[PDB]
Image (cartoon, rainbow, N blue to C red; front, side):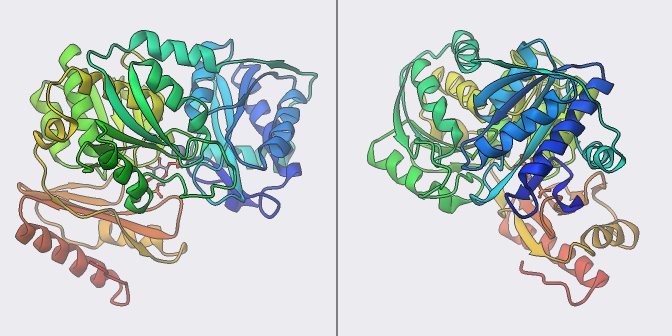
Length: 454
Ligand SMILES: O=P([O-])(O)O[C@H]1O[C@H](COP(=O)(O)O)[C@@H](O)[C@H](O)[C@H]1O
Ligand SMILES: [Zn+2]
């Protein structure tokens, strides 16, 4: 089924669209692709899902039947798998994960020879299977215990000044295997919330991008008078943040704090953010002498862009934050949490006042309009072709973004759902609704039937 080969990764329903047999052939396809790039060595990890044991053995056998040398790192967060692919012999790795999709989902995040696959590169794996353009060989499997290396890597490079008390919510995802322990080892007291790994995800699904999944966290932070709240998503490559007073700090505001710190030590450094992030981030980066690079949404696309630009830091609005400075340049919520605590601990102000000090504007959440999968990209192309946007700085690298003096707006197509994704920001509520109006008029110009929920 080509439907499981997605823009950023592979994702399927275990049994239905993703079976044991398909996991094997995906392994052969990846192993074959790795060998074609001259990399026999592949690390393999999995998240906390129930299907993980079943499917990962098939992934591994697929790799091994190509002649690949597999390093099995067991059940780890996604960033720990990316880490393994940076410190072991090979620069390839596959993470078996369904991230924060419902329990029955699983999938693959794939790096081959240092490069995170996306778009045509993921299609190329399906194509190898169909064509039987597959390597055959007698590979090897080695058990590798990678967590302690990861844990010590971070701990030894992080220096907190003051002690902090932190609520850590892992939503019963695999971040529980290390984030509470690592964070404590930095010099914090950790209040654990849903830190037990449970593939059933009994409490709230680990999706920090939705405020409903941060309610328990916010509540505990306040109840325990904690210095900060942290939530990790299913596989640990997203982080969500809450202040001592329960304010949700969206990832583009988090990136402002990170950009200030990275740019400070690294004059001129390129800093990447996706099209969903506040314009205030463009200003800030530039004001500290950095180079802002706006790019496409999607972690694979962002990681590729970091290689093309030499960026020292990237972030997406969904909460993937990619440090190259002092790190390896992959997205990692657990490392980003540590880098955050390091910065906050130097400050005599509480976390609410650190973040409230930066400019904040009136801002919508991410807005979604469900359209048909047939129509979503065409709608955008129509907006790019047909629509007169004047006027503002118009960016078309991913959807249509328009930047004005006192605000901005975005419409893009999701690469994971049949939806249009919108965000609007302005200095004032008045300006915000004026930008909303323009976008609503332009969508209804393409198709008067289109839902416009804003
Ligand atoms: O969970 P992941 O690792 O696949 O991460 C991906 O999930 C979402 C799907 O993107 P889209 O807006 O195109 O649907 C994005 O918001 C996020 O930025 C991206 O990295
Ligand atoms: Zn994730």
